[PDB]
Length: 213
Length: 151
Image 1 (cartoon, rainbow over the protein chains, first blue to last red):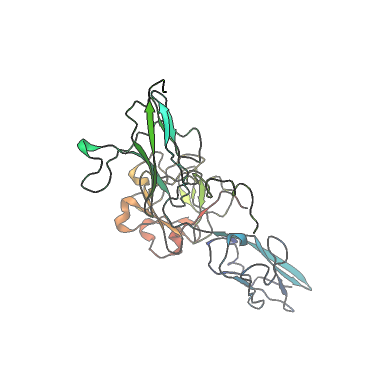
Image 2 (cartoon, chains in turn yellow, green):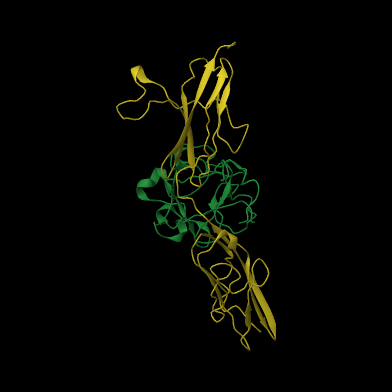
């Protein structure tokens, strides 16, 4: 009859961890005679190389050491202690994340230059993966009395109201201009800020009258 | 080399606006999912079903962020004592400073009491940790985001 030599230390099956970092799943036991330790992935025999990097479990320490973990490893791992007089088993659910310690990444082409009639109401978009809480802003490349670039060598701009709300896409980042006089013809920038530096794209808008050619 | 459609026709190979969706705030210390109890007190829990672990973050400025629940609307905060509660209104008491530590774990520092380095960790049993109680280095303060459900 087998038993968990260390029960108290076995209620933590949730093991959320960062990628490429060795993991050690164990569950100490004993009995008469020494019971076997069976493993499995998701719920079926976990081969001693059942995956890349392979494993190296110490069937003696009642452990299952895995190195350089990967999201593809995230899977409720279960230990099985079977003995002639009894068979016990407990399961640990593993996960693996891959943090993106960068600035916000913004799909290209977005925003993208566009045109519109006066009094036309427009939008500009922005996809932004960004693990770290981003702080997206929409600038307007205004030109302070004379030049577009001030003594800081960096362009003059102005944060924009927001023009509306969420609505459309809960995955995008639009800016909605409305009566678009031949005054919003400047350049618009999407400045995605982040704990880890800033990222950003830009684009142009051009507005004309009502006939043409 | 396998692959699929979608990413092959995509225009961006990362989940767009993924910061808008809500997530759980694990805690490297125990195995808990930060919880802002309906009443208003905060604590730990493993119950991957606890209807009060679904946090919705956001940043009004770089690095500074609000931690919030998707059930109520409690703007988690830290009182002058070092107690994490859950204001109903957004206020200086509820602004945290987020940072992705080399151990790829995030840490929240009570912006207001930043100077003293008070974190939003969780004491082993899973109970909230008194501000002053935290120390930069203890797993208690090492939180690690998680998707609402498994896969």
